Image (spheres, helix red, strand yellow):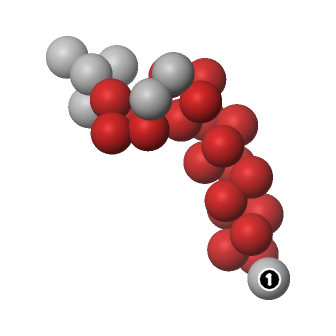
Amino acid sequence: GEDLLKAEELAAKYRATGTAPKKILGIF
């Protein structure tokens, strides 16, 4: 499943932000 890869990606990205919903915070 590539949604698991996406889950890795989001884990690579969002955790890079520090907190997933703060994906908008990075934009703030």
Q: Is residue 1 above or below residue 21?
A: below
Residue located 34% across and 19% down the image: 26
Residue 8 visible from this viewpoint: yes
Residue 27 visible from this viewpoint: no
Q: Residues within 10 Å of mark 1 (few under 14, many from 20)?
A: few
Q: Secondary structure at mark 1?
A: loop
Q: Is residue 22 above or below residue 26?
A: below
In the picture of the structure, the residue carrying the numbered disc 1 is 1
Query: Extreme front residue here?
Result: 19
Q: Is residue 12 left or right of residue 27?
A: right
Residue located 68% across and 74% down the image: 3
Query: Which percent across, then down, holds residue 28?
Result: 20, 17
Query: Which percent across, then down, holds residue 4?
Result: 74, 69
Query: Which percent across, then down, holds residue 8?
Result: 74, 52
Query: Which percent across, then down, holds residue 9?
Result: 69, 49
Q: Is residue 10 above or below residue 18?
A: below
**Residue type at mark 1?**
Gly
Q: Quadrant of residue 22?
A: top left
Q: Quadrant of residue 2?
A: bottom right
Query: What is the quadrant of the N terminus in the image?
Result: bottom right
Q: How many marks?
A: 1
Q: Is residue 1 left or right of residue 18?
A: right
Query: Extreme bottom residue here?
Result: 1
